[PDB]
Image: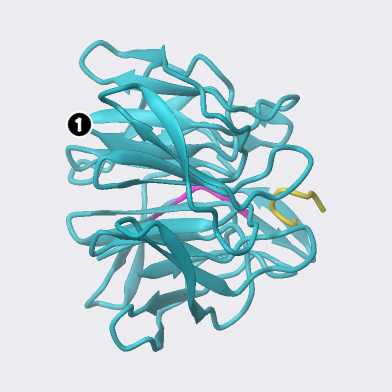
Amino acid sequence: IYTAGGYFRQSLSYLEAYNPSDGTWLRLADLQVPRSGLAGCVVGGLLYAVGGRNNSPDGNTDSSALDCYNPMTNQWSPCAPMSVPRNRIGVGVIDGHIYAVGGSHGCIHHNSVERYEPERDEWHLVAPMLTRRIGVGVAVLNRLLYAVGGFDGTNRLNSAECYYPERNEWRMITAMNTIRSGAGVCVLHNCIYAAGGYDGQDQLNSVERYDVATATWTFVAPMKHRRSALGITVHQGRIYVLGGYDGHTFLDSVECYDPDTDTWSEVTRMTSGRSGVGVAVT
Amino acid sequence: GDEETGE
């Protein structure tokens, strides 16, 4: 479990790895620009950091950057930047290709989406979403791209839509039961999970999951601690959520979801509390 | 600086 970037009074350069077996934290090479509100993913075994923002005492620069971490070089390397800066981006990987979804640049909330090819180092625009979405959760299932929740600049969203690559088109699907911006969104086997987030009034601990075969969202066991802007990933068939903000403190808590008994429990404590991280596994 | 992310 690798977490990159994040926010704790300023955007951070931390790259750290958590081990669910031995429970100890590995501290690794720093990002070559601090970022929060970024997304992380893995392609070809290399970890990509996508978008985000450097919120510092001397600036607040939205990031168009794409950069590559190699787990046995302990080295970061820059890749081609995106069309636009995307703070609070979501990403998903189809066929080893990078889809960058939504996010913001200043007051502009993107509905734009663009595709990166790792072995060509190229971005190009695809069809935009039906909705402008920042803090969108993104997941991939059955070679389809799902954009879930988010914020359009005015309303926070329970809607979700689906991208079909070979038709270049977005399809609205059944909305979530809960409005969520900055939730953790991932696949645990074959339910698209949406955990936590912010509905414009409170940070959430509720978790719900989408069943494609019935096009139904159903609620499962909620987290122990409400959290928004959390990282999320699935390891060994279990879901891990990392940090976030609960309206009062930047959480270092990390929770595990065991799907077969449907319970959450405290697994570990991050080295420092933070929100807005990028998380991925390799 | 906002309730969703803490920033």
Magenta span has A153?
Answer: no
Residue A111 at x, y = what percent?
54, 22
Q: Which residue is mark 1?
A: A142
Taking the spot 39% from the left edge, 25% from the top edge, the residue there is A216
Amino acid type, residue under disc 1 in the picture: Asn
Residue B3 at x, y = what percent?
78, 50
Q: Is residue A133 shown above or below A87?
A: above
Of A79 and A179, which appears nearest the observer?
A179
Of A16 and A227, which appears nearest the observer?
A227
Q: Is residue A12 left or right of residue A100?
A: right
Magenta span of residues: A49-53
Residue furthest front as drawn? A261
Let me know if residue A185 appears in the view.
yes
Quadrant of the rendering where the N terminus of chain A is positioned:
bottom left
Tell me the SS state at disc 1. Answer: loop
- Which color was chain B given? yellow
- Which color was chain A given? cyan
Let me know if residue A116 appears in the view.
no
**Label 1 crowd bin: few (<14), some (14–19), many (20+), radius 10 Å:** few
Taking the spot 65% from the left edge, 57% from the top edge, the residue there is A226
- Decide whether the magenta segment is chiefly helix, strand or loop: strand
Q: Is residue A250 left or right of residue A237?
A: right
Residue A91 at x, y = what percent?
40, 41
Residue A174 at x, y = what percent?
45, 19
Q: Is residue A194 left or right of residue A178?
A: left
Taking the spot 79% from the left edge, 49% from the top edge, the residue there is B2
